[PDB]
Every structure is written in structure tokens, then in C-alpha cells.
Image 1 (cartoon, each protein chain N blue to C red):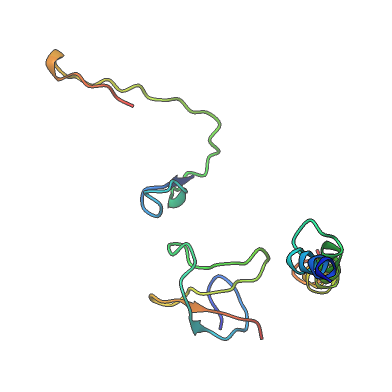
Image 2: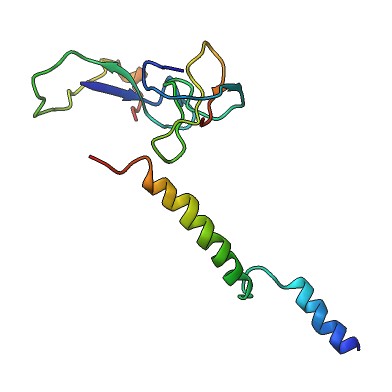
Length: 49
Length: 49
Length: 49
């Protein structure tokens, strides 16, 4: 119980930054946010001749 | 010909900004540094940066 | 608005305080201007439509 709770305790403290899964999560939010907003910023202003 | 200085817009930081456009439309190809000498007397001699 | 420098459609607000302040615009990493200058002399930061 104290070792289970100790395990969950280090599971509380550790998200950033060296703990991917979490960098996979921000790879996802930065993925679709990057695609949406940043690709839409490439699409407009500017493309054409 | 465009002249730039840090003096008027960023005196303390050094970024250069345009302060003049001179009506010189013949392309400048050459330049030289004009030597200056300071006609001090011996006891008034300074060092110049 | 229609500034001498550029066209555009924006909602000016008296914002603070980021810029160059001697040439007039401010961009944000793209073609757009976000956006104060020009008024005399205040910070009318613009936005998209």
C-alpha cells in the first residue's frame, strides 16, 4: 500500500519533460495545433505570385 | 543612400534605425575613410577610440 | 482602417506597449500587423476581422 502509493506519488510528480508519454501528448496537441494554425498560416499570407 | 544610427531610437542598446535618405542615385561603388588628425598641443593630447 | 502603409480591416484598441515607436507598425512573424500605429501618438493595436 505505501509502495503502491509511492508509485502513484512519483506518477503525480513526473510529467515534464523527460517522461514521454507526456511529450507524446504535446506532440499531439502541437501536432494538430501545428497543422491547423500553422499550416493555415502557410496557406494564407503568403502563397501566390 | 540610406543612413542608419542607433543614436535616436536605441541610444543605450545599439539597434540601428534609418535617419536619412540622401538623393544620391548614381550607384556608390567605392568608399574610403577620411583620415582626421587632432591639432592639439603636446599637453592636450588625448587618445581617440 | 486604411493606413498609408497598408490596407486592412481591424478593431483598434488602446493596448500596451510593445513596438519600435519610431517607425510606425508592428508585425507578428508574418505579413500581418498586430497592429498599432498609426495614431498620434497612441497604441491602437489592431486585430483580424
